[PDB]
Image (cartoon, rainbow, N blue to C red):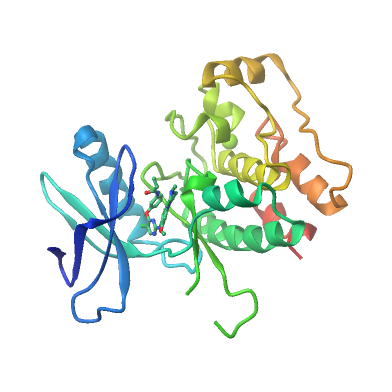
Length: 269
Ligand SMILES: CCC(=O)Nc1cccc(Oc2nc(Nc3ccc(N4CCN(C)CC4)cc3OC)ncc2Cl)c1
Ligand SMILES: [Mg+2]
């Protein structure tokens, strides 16, 4: 039993062991029914793990939202960092998709409405996530309201503030979810995240990536050679969902849907 402020956990109660964090279940030390997740350095990748967890503290201490995993406390030192976070008892979207194979439009809509709510806060704060993918979208059952299941965006280790007249250029994220401009080593902005979201939505709908390749390098070459990208959308797809996907999965960020359009899109009614 280790303690971090008013919280405790045991390293028996593993949640998961990523390359840049190890996460354990724990609880408040007074209020034992308040569950938490405690994120720790992965010493196999100490320097990078420490950097990412420090960056996550900097971003998350500024974000309170129902659809973003909450940072309850943290403890940063020269050689160790801990985050104490809201426990998401439903696990990740990736595991859910692995079981469901595909999601109905109504479920996509429920989840996407919540993601958009989170993204509205990020966009208003000038923050880009840069690693949106099903492994970083968590589910929580916190319930006498309709559709009480909650989506929570996690893993802000790669996120940054981006001033509204500036472009980012750091290469980070997961190749299969990365916007073309990102993986082609160009300058990008907040619309890179909208591509990632479009690819998650497409994956939920069809069970596949919109643009398949054998490796990151292959996917890059594919985007380089194809000046327009058109995802294959099933004929059964509703017209608002088809239009949303086509507007999100535009190769060129200038042509891609922007935030205001995304938040007010007919599909999300
Ligand atoms: C390798 C999986 C992992 O550790 N992934 C992850 C990714 C992002 C954040 C995170 O931390 C948290 N995880 C949870 N919950 C949670 C997260 C992941 C799972 N998995 C993921 C897939 N595995 C195959 C099974 C369990 C189970 C979980 O509960 C039940 N709740 C709060 C935080 Cl801060 C953990
Ligand atoms: Mg961009």
